[PDB]
Structure formats: structure tokens, C-alpha cells
Amino acid sequence: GSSGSSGVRAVRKDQTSKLKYVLQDARFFLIKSNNHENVSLAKAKGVWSTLPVNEKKLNLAFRSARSVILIFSVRESGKFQGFARLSSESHHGGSPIHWVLPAGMSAKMLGGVFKIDWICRRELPFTKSAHLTNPWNEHKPVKIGRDGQEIELECGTQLCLLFPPDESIDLYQVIHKMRH
């Protein structure tokens, strides 16, 4: 072409910005489970069911805030099981999947189903997360917490970056839907 005179001010070439953007000013929610079957199933169908309180909570925080991240952490596992940003609120169409509940919990408590878009199909050892500190409690590490505990911004962010690079998921598509 022609007339391409431009004074560059800054150059970039990484896949961390988009990732940190999809959660830019978003609310992180730490969800703990009691089995791997749930995680796998959630990653297979691409959904995740939970108590009603958590559903309405995420919905309000979602419409009230930008995005809602959900870090998956397995108890007695010694590492995370990945994560996923709430691509949308819950649902109540047909019916939920045949989740794997114990001999006591009721599927009716799970309420509806949520649509999570797994951005990272990998794992993360607690060793890499063994350093962060969530001031939203008592300056304690992220390794400490229960199911359904809010997390700061820096905490969740760093925790996410820790995860390995993904080359089997469309990250841009997650940002394109937002802008449009």
C-alpha cells in the first residue's frame, strides 16, 4: 500500500492479555468438590450444577459486575482441576444431567445448570499457588478456604496465569462475544 508512516509507541506479542481481559474487573468464585467424576463430567458436557444460593449469587454478581470466574479445586487432591469463566447465567430448560451425588444429597438442590466455557483444559499444582495471599480474610494463602468463598482480583488473576498455555481452546472467541 502507501502512506504507512506511523511512530510505534509500544509492541506486544503474548496470549496473557486476552486472558487477563476476559476476567478484567471480574469476580472470582472458588468452588470445591468431593470427587473427580464431577470435574470430568463438567468438562465433558461443559456445564456445572450447584446449590441454589450459589446460582442466584453468581447471577447477581454477574449482571452487577463484568464477569464471574470459577476456579475448580479438588479437596485432598493437592492441586487444582482447572477453571472456567461464567459464559452466562443458569438455565431451566429441559433438565440437568445425571450428576454423581452421594446417598444423601438431592439433585433438586442443584437447581438449574450453568454454562461454563473452559478456557484452560489443564491442571495446576498447589506448589505454584503456594505463595499468593488473599487479604480478604486474614492475609491467608489461597490454599486455604471453603466451597463458595469469594476471592480478590490479584489472587485469582495470578492463580490463573500460573496455569500452563492452552492450544485447544478459542480464547479470542470469548472476548469477541463480549464486545459484540
Image (spheres, helix red, strand yellow):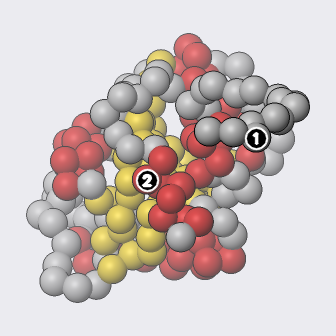
- Residue furthest out toward the left: 98
Question: Which residue occupies 36% across, 28% down?
Answer: 167
37 or 61, nearer to the observer: 61
Amino acid type at circle 1 is: Ser
Q: Mark 1 sits on what residue?
A: 3
- In the rendered view, tell whether residue 78 sits above or below residue 107: above
Q: What number of labels is visible?
A: 2
Q: Position of residue 179 (x, y in %)?
A: 59, 65
Q: Are marks 2 and 1 in contact (CB under 8 Å)?
A: no
Which of the pair 4/93 is nearer the observer? 4
Residue 148 visible in the displayed image:
no
Q: Earlier in the sequence, mark 2 or mark 1?
A: 1
| Side (left or right) of 61 relative to 103 | right
Task: Answer yes or no: is residue 49 visible.
Answer: yes
Specify the quadrant of the image occupied by residue 119: top left
**What's the amino acid at mark 2?**
Gln
Q: Residue furthest front?
A: 2
The spot of residue 38 in percent (x, y) is 25, 48
Crowding at dot 1, Cα within 10 Å, few <14 / some 14-19 / many 20+, comes out as few
Which residue is rendered at x = 18% and y = 59% of the image? 99
Residue 33 coordinates in the image, percent (x, y): 37, 46
Residue 89 to residue 157: above or below? below
Q: Nearer the viewer, mark 2 or mark 1?
A: 1
Give me the C-alpha separation between circle 2 and circle 1.
32 Å
Question: What kind of element bears circle 1?
Answer: loop
- Residue plotted at (33% across, 80% down): 91
Considering only vertical position in the picture, is 16 above or below 114?
above
Residue displayed at 62% across by 39% down: 1
What mark, if any, has residue 173 been given in the picture? Answer: 2
Label 2, secondary structure: give it.
helix
x then y, percent, for residue 63: 61, 78
User: Camera-side residue: 81 or 52?
Assistant: 81
